[PDB]
Image (tube, coloured by chain):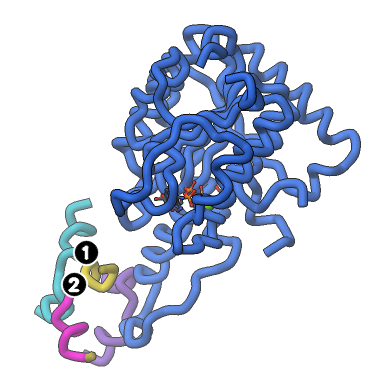
Chain colours: A purple, B cyan, C yellow, D blue
Amino acid sequence: YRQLVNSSFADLQ
Amino acid sequence: RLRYRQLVNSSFADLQK
Amino acid sequence: RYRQLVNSSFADLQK
Amino acid sequence: RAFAKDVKRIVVKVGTAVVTGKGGRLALGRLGAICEQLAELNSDGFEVILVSSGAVGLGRQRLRYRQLVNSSFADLQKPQMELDGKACAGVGQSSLMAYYETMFDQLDVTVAQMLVTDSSFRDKDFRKQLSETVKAMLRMRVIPVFNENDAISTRRTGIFWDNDSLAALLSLELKADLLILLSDVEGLYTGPPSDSTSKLIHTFIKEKHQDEITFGEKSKLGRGGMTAKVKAAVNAAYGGVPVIITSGYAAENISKVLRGLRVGTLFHQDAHLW
Ligand SMILES: Nc1ncnc2c1ncn2[C@@H]1O[C@H](COP(=O)(O)OP(=O)(O)OP(=O)(O)O)[C@@H](O)[C@H]1O
Ligand SMILES: N[C@@H](CCC(=O)O)C(=O)O
Ligand SMILES: [Mg+2]
């Protein structure tokens, strides 16, 4: 989660 | 392109599942 | 402040 | 409107309001109609010089989305600050020239990116070379797209930091016949158009329409709004260029003005003998 909350929409891509 | 659209429309609570 | 952002969509944040 | 017969060099001007509609989105509806009308005019033997504006809005919108895509969720916590005082402008001018090309490559009319600063102007020997260049470019049936470079400037006299005045100066320098100032409203009213007290006028008399023109209780400032527009028009008229202010949310109007159908407001140096 923290990773998800500390990620870039570009990263999420 | 469709993956981009899906990610643009998704809700953060949906990026976990 | 938090919950909204959590459930909102990247598009939405662009309002 | 008798001058409409003998005009073969016009300087139209689309303001940011005309170009952009919602959320830094090019008004494809308005811009397309205006470009189509300009292409039809060009074909009918008319030197059409286009002075456009709206790069700042497009740059602001695209740099917004280029922040949120490259932002961390934590960042989304606090409303982001100003994007920039000049970079939005840069990106937006790029985008606008891009659009124009794409559109003018459908009706086969070539355009050139001529960007001029206030310092470049006022430089002796510049007010000429620009002149000659623009003349040759018009001669090969090309439509220039003038603008004010807001990305390499240092202002943060001469041009009035507005394309509207830029239009005026260029028109006087390039020795144009007419300068059109397409805007959102149907012309120069007697104040704010919302209330019924303000009434549209059709000719700007020097000593008549300078007592009931507040330019809105609202002072635009950013684009100088109307006051600036009226000033530009007056200056252009005085130098020897008739100037007409008209709505731009309807391109068809341009043909009516050029053909002569009593539409808009006239800022003519022949006010006494009219
Ligand atoms: N005296 C007036 N009569 C009619 N409308 C007015 C008056 N004063 C202010 N306004 C309003 O303010 C606005 C001023 O428009 P403005 O000239 O700033 O747009 P613009 O030409 O796109 O500016 P720019 O291109 O420099 O960004 C008009 O849309 C008009 O509705
Ligand atoms: N900065 C905008 C125009 C600024 C203005 O409204 O005059 C551009 O370069 O296109
Ligand atoms: Mg203005």
Depth check, front residue: D25 or D73: D25
Q: Residue furthest right?
A: D124
User: How many numbered discs?
Assistant: 2
Callout 2: chain: C
Specify the quadrant that holds the C terminus of chain D.
Answer: top right
Residue B8's tag is 1
Image side of residue B13 versus residue D164, left or right: left
**Secondary structure found at label 2:** loop
Q: Are marks 2 and 1 in contact (CB under 8 Å)?
A: yes
Q: Main secondary structure of the magenta part?
A: helix
**Secondary structure found at label 1:** helix
Residue at 52%, 29% in the rendered image: D266
Q: Position of residue D31 (x, y in %)?
A: 38, 35
Disc 1 Cβ-to-ligand 2 distance below 8 Å: no
Callout 1: chain: B
Q: Amino acid at mark 2?
A: Ser
Q: Which residues fall within the magenta stretch?
A: C2-8
Image side of residue C2 versus residue D253, left or right: left
Residue at 71%, 47% in the rendered image: D159
Q: Amino acid at mark 1?
A: Val
Depth check, front residue: D173 or C2: D173
Q: Position of residue D253 (x, y in %)?
A: 37, 25
The residue beneath circle 2 is C9
* Crowd around label 1: few <14 · some 14–19 · many ≥20 (10 Å): some
Visible residue check, residue D187: yes
**Occupied quadrant, residue D169:** top right
**Alpha-carbon distance for marks 2 and 1?**
7 Å
Residue D164's tag is none
Q: Position of residue D117 (x, y in %)?
A: 72, 47
Residue at 61%, 49% in the rendered image: D162
Q: Is residue D249 magenta?
A: no
Q: Position of residue D153 (x, y in %)?
A: 71, 56
